[PDB]
Image (tube, rainbow, N blue to C red; front, side):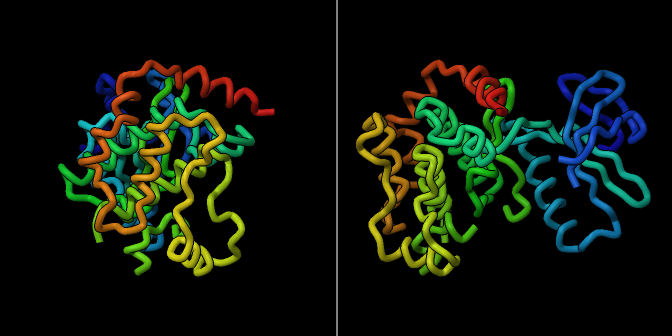
Length: 272
C-alpha cells in the first residue's frame, strides 16, 4: 500500500525518486523513473490535527474511488517517520481560475461536459460510499490539458453556494450549489456578487427569486431548464442526482463530441 506509484503501470518508488518542482502543502513533482509529473500532498505528523484529519478523510474517499473516472485519483503513498506523501494525478486548474483566465462567460458546451462529469461524480459518491460532498463550487471542479473534468478533494465529504433548506439535510443542497456554480461560470458573474457579508448572501438566497440563466445569451432550453431545476427553492421538490441524470441536458452531453482539450489549451495560452 505504501512505496509504489501506479499510473497505468506499477513502479516501486520512494520519496527520493521524486523531484520537487515547487508548490501549487501540495507540490508538483516529477517521478524521475518515468518523467510523469504528479501532484503530491505532504502531510506532516507535526501538522494541525484538524488539517491532517481532513487530508486523511479526503484520502480515504479518494482511495475508495478508483472505479470513478470523474474523481481525481491517488497514484500512491510514501510514509516516513515524520511525513506522509500522497501522490495524486496533477490537473491543470479549477473552474474558478478558468473563469478569471477567460475574463468572461464559459461556453455552454464546456459547461455541459462539466455538468455530466460533476453530477456523475457526486452521484457515485452518494450511491457507493454514502458521501454527500457538501461543498460544490467552481474551485472544486478540475480540468486538464487532456479534456478531463473531475471533482477535487472532499476533506469534509462555502456560504454562498448554500441551499435554502441548509440555511433554514440531503444531497439536494449540493444540487443547489451546482446550480449557482453553473450560473456563475455561464454568465461570468457570481449571482450574489453585490453582497458584503455571508449572512447577506443567505438573505438573498431566501428572499429573492432563484438566479436563473439569462434569456438573451443563446443558452439552450435544455441548459436553462437544467439550471431552473437545480435552483428550485423548495428542497422538497428539488431533483436528486437520480432524476438529474435523465435530464435532456445531461443526455445531450453524454453523447455530444466537444473538444474540451483544445478549448482548454487555448484558454490557458491566453495566459496573457
